[PDB]
Amino acid sequence: CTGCVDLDELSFEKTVERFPYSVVKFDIAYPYGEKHEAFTAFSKSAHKATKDLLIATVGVKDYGELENKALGDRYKVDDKNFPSIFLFKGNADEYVQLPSHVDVTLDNLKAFVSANTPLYIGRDGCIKEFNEVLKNYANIPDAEQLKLIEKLQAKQEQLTDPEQQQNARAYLIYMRKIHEVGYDFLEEETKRLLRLKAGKVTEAKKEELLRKLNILEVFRVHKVTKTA
Image (cartoon, rainbow, N blue to C red; front, side):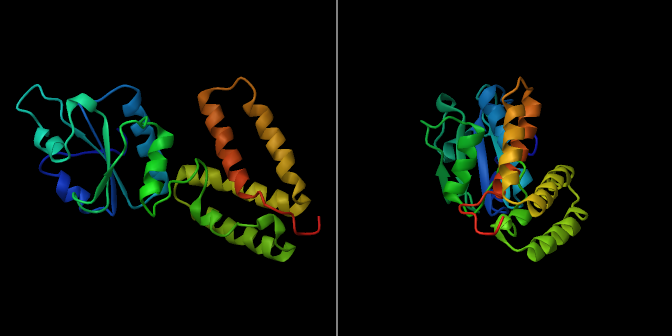
């Protein structure tokens, strides 16, 4: 899969022991089907979020000389219950296995990581470095919102990643609209977005409305503090 590093007997221990955290799927050789695709979707989203995570696969598939059987055997897994998901904390030795009763899904995969690490794979659309400075945005003074608008605008102009650049535009538009009209903007843009989402939409268009609603969610406050 994309971003997934496939490992073997020679490279596995050495590669896992070079990243602070590793998520490995053991499965047949040449994997396919829905669980492998959920792992593929996990691998892409995990890269979007993190510097520090190895996403990796090991093929076992026992029909020949037996590639990687000894590696599956180290971690006690079996053609009989593939896929098996392991999370390692920096060496081949400190690992947690995803419970077999747990469906291998994007959602469970992300939960598996933050459950067991200081890593956080964020919501599709979020930019951690924008989120880090925008708590309570709607409630802070005109003058600080204006300087946050200026600080994030300069950050936006230095982003090198295409999806980050697009997601930043939506942060800045929300920032500016909230500064201009106040907390009532949240409800207006939620109603706008949710009306489109409740339409007949493609998978790809849904995802992109979800990116905006997750960005928008950043700006919700628990209480309204600032004079409207």
